[PDB]
Image (cartoon, grey):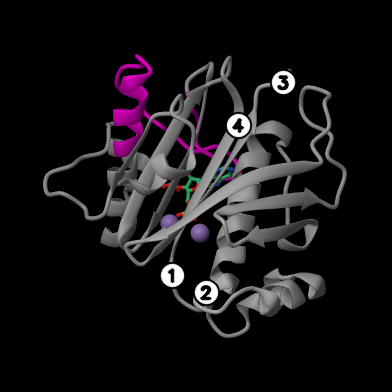
């Protein structure tokens, strides 16, 4: 029934909460990151890390702070990859072991039309044509946006480089899959090359959730 579990493999534990339950707290090492933050930001940060620590516990990893790096990226324990996302109505996290997957990214968005002007900023001309050809009944613009954000989250842990919206062509299939084709140099930190990702998506509870797993090499 959970959205993330529906779009990632079983060997990546996930956890999600739709509200901020009363009484949660950051770990002491995390408090400085939100010390001067408004309540909505404090809450999404605290609740998502509760979810992340629940999922880490399934992998056998005990309570640990999840700090942020220079580009905002979550800093996981050695040997762990993961992703976190929050929007109104959703906090969720997924983690996995580097011996079992290379990278994971997720992103949750409300299932609504994009704000005025956003599609023109984030979509390639060809993508706009492709979305207009998809079947009526789904906010394909928001899905494309969500999928591109997930593409960056799966890419960054492997490359330590920026990926702009114009740097990848995402093709959405109505069947709950998508692909991301990288249009820039795909050199990865370990010397391999990234060229394309396979993604999964689900719409439920008024939300879009997209996920990419970069699988283990053969
Ligand atoms: O909400 P969103 O879907 O936009 O995801 C935001 C999260 O993406 C993650 N994130 C931010 N920058 C990132 C990056 N460069 N690479 C991967 N994940 C990143 C963070 O965990 C952030 O949540 P936090 O600031 O509470 O840690
Ligand atoms: Mn968020
Ligand atoms: Mn998003």
Query: Which residue position is annotated with label 1?
Result: 111
What residue do we see at 83% from left, 32% from top? 193
| Left or right side of 211 for 20 | left
Taking the image as drawn, is residue 38 in sight? no
Q: From mark 2 to mark 4, how far is it between C-alphas? A: 27 Å
Crowding at mark 2 (Cα within 10 Å: few <14, some 14-19, many 20+): some
Q: Are marks 3 and 4 in contact (CB under 8 Å)?
A: no
Of pointers 3 and 1, the one earlier in the residue sequence: 1
Q: Are marks 1 and 2 in contact (CB under 8 Å)?
A: yes
Query: Which residue position is annotated with label 4?
Result: 103
Q: From mark 1 to mark 4, how far is it between C-alphas? A: 25 Å
Helix, strand or loop under label 2: loop
Dot 1 beta carbon under 8 Å from ligand 3? no
The quadrant in which residue 90 appears is: bottom left
Query: Which residue position is annotated with label 3?
Result: 217
* Towards the viewer: 111 or 134: 134
Q: From mark 3 to mark 2, how far is it between C-alphas? A: 34 Å
Mark 1 or 4, closer to the camera: 1
What residue do we see at 32% from left, 48% from top? 35
Helix, strand or loop under label 3: loop
Of pointers 2 and 4, the one earlier in the residue sequence: 4
The residue segment tinted magenta is 51-76
């Amino acid at each position: 029934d959970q959205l993330i579990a529906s779009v990632v493999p079983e060997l990546l534990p996930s956890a999600e909460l739709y509200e901020d339950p009363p009484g949660l707290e950051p770990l002491p090492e995390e408090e400085p990151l939100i010390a001067k933050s408004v309540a909505k930001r404090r809450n999404e940060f605290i609740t998502v890390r509760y979810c992340a620590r629940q999922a880490l516990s399934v992998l056998g990893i005990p309570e640990v702070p999840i700090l942020k790096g220079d580009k905002g990226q979550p800093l996981w324990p050695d040997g762990i990859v993961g992703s976190m996302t929050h929007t109104e109505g959703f906090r969720g996290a997924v983690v996995g072991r580097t011996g079992e997957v290379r990278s994971v990214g997720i992103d949750a968005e409300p299932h609504d039309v994009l704000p005025n002007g956003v599609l023109k900023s984030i979509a390639l001309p060809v993508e706009r044509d492709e979305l207009d050809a998809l079947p009526a009944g789904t906010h394909w613009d928001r899905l494309l946006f969500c999928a591109k954000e997930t593409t960056y989250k799966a890419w960054f842990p492997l490359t330590a480089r920026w990926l702009g919206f114009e740097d990848a062509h995402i093709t959405i299939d109505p069947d709950g899959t998508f692909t991301s084709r990288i249009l820039v140099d795909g050199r990865a930190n370990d010397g391999t090359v990234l060229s394309a990702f396979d993604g999964r998506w689900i719409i439920d509870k008024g939300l879009i959730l997209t996920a990419i797993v970069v699988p283990k090499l053969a």
